[PDB]
Image 1 (cartoon, rainbow over the protein chains, first blue to last red):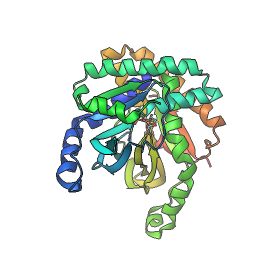
Image 2: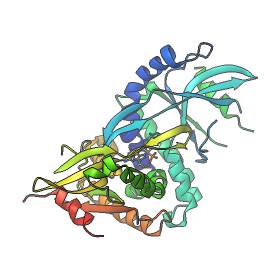
Image 3: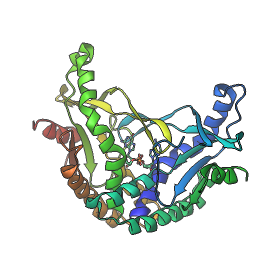
Image 4: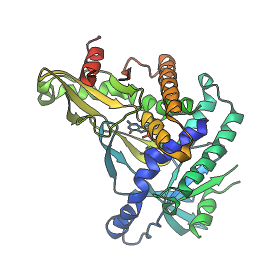
Length: 174
Length: 177
Ligand SMILES: Nc1nc(=O)c2ncn([C@@H]3O[C@@H]4COP(=O)(O)O[C@@H]5[C@@H](O)[C@H](n6cnc7c(N)ncnc76)O[C@@H]5COP(=O)(O)O[C@@H]3[C@@H]4O)c2[nH]1
């Protein structure tokens, strides 16, 4: 299926590569690049999984972009020093800072949305919802048995006055 | 199907983003005379599509010699600000002498197909892999044929496996202006 391939590519080509190094990158940021009065970046990659596949290019009102982690580079598929970058976000609640975390949308959901938009893909909006859920289930089952493993990332799936900050804060507060 | 999603993934999240800016990046590189004294970088992105899905991480080691990187291109995508896209320049040797210079890379989704055939949890046989790899290439060509970003700035190089010369494979396409 469509979602089966997207989920395995998200793991094979991304999570498997950046999860084993995420802990070292976050500890580097907290010790050197963090401003004096800014909070420790929580561990773990928080992955946003909107089932409607609505992915804005700019995630950054209670979610404010702070900074980027140090880059991770590697050679892949003949591209020398392919760069992997992640963004740190501040989470506001009642005007007060409630958390800071590495946060991003699952990029394959943008592919599912584009396929529903383009007639040549032959892919309906109903197909999109079924495949989005199937993507999330496959990714969870992959991570459950993955050595790089689910303990470096949290999947935040949700369907849609929904508040995205409160959704992430609920996961960030255990 | 598996290949259907990977092809659209390759177009939506990569080719449609870098192909419209590729010509201007190569031109800027060729405008520096110390770069050009090596040899000029040909236009177009040359995409290697081995049907067996054997994709090494280092193509230079695998008559194909890494030269330099093309200046990076950045953009904001899915909440990752200033995501970095990079491409590499290779010179192709023939009888010990440089015969061509081009931007060259494997299609990264073929490594997903390979890894799926390797992992039992994917439920994906080697027969499945060959079928989907051919479906991937056809679906990618049909997308590029109708893509406004267009296939006039990229070349697909599909092949399988006697001595096989990848450098000669690319050189045959590179010499077809
Ligand atoms: N050669 C090459 N250089 C690149 O910079 C690049 N960036 C993307 N792609 C390929 O285009 C297609 C779609 O791009 P994504 O949705 O962003 O990647 C999807 C995306 O779900 C995720 N991902 C990969 N790199 C990521 C990154 N740097 N940041 C966030 N997510 C990423 O993991 C998938 C597999 O990645 P790749 O298997 O490396 O190949 C991709 C894919 O085939 C690239 N291909």
